[PDB]
Image (cartoon, rainbow, N blue to C red):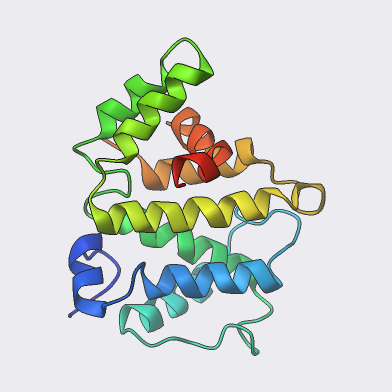
Amino acid sequence: GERVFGCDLGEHLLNSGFEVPQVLQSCTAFIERYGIVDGIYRLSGVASNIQRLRHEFDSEHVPDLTKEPYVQDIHSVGSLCKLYFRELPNPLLTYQLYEKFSDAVSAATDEERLIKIHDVIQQLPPPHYRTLEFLMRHLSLLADYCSITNMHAKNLAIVWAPNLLRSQSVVVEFILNHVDVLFS
């Protein structure tokens, strides 16, 4: 189409043919291999570096992040990944389900929260469902490395939630902590 950043997620995936966005695949693949570092997603890239990457991906060009000059500035990749989500015109968790997600996590026990959160996730439209599963599995994998990155699930969810769920980090942390059962 005409652009990637700011394009509705469903429209973008209809256009590209990918299960989840190429930019998400590229950023996560890079981070999982080369970005297992202190402060992943906490620290930020240099703005000029983020805008360069944005401009490339926004043209549907896939830059080779694993080669210089990209391979050095890990945090521009993490920043870019978050920014893709921040610019979606309908957030990842969707406007339609925003209140249901909040209410779900407000249940009194983890069992009831699990059931209620599950029921909300199951009504996400397919492009949102697939993209959320892929992101949550990436952040769960990263949380395994928390002794290196100093990024536990709680802090991953705090940095991420504003980009994903808007009209909150409790909802995102709960999904992250239960990704295997919620996407089984």
